[PDB]
Picture 1: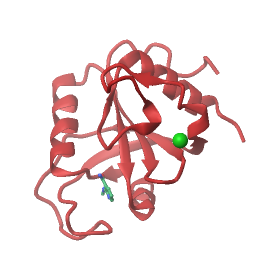
Picture 2: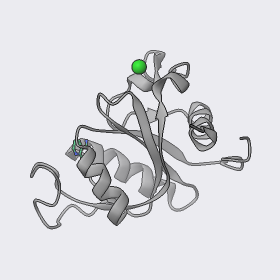
Picture 3: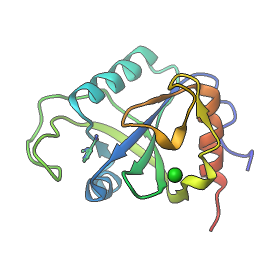
Length: 150
Ligand SMILES: CNc1ncccc1C(N)=O
Ligand SMILES: [Cl-]
């Protein structure tokens, strides 16, 4: 409630969209994630180019659910050669560490009035997986999620 996510001077924020809620449950249990091949490459470049100077945040949402389900920070580069078949389907190859910060359902109603100037001014709730969020809009999103209460 303005107590959250001030002093976020640098850093970068991405939307994660999963059509497997089981995969997200596993992320929360073991603090790891895996995206598509092109998604992993985008997150890998953001994390590496940050060179530790700032956080990379991930805003998670289950496709079709109508709500965001929480926030985690990237905590490692992407390892592309890892054990196969750990996710809901075999097509997900690789792994990076994350640290979950919030696990809570925030309805899209609370966020849909934030639009992305880098995505044709579309609402942030209408994003695809690994859509990057401009820093000032991300700060608005993170703060709404942080303070939202049932
Ligand atoms: C492991 N990750 C996933 N699982 C299921 C559906 C989408 C994803 C994704 N784009 O990250
Ligand atoms: Cl909606």
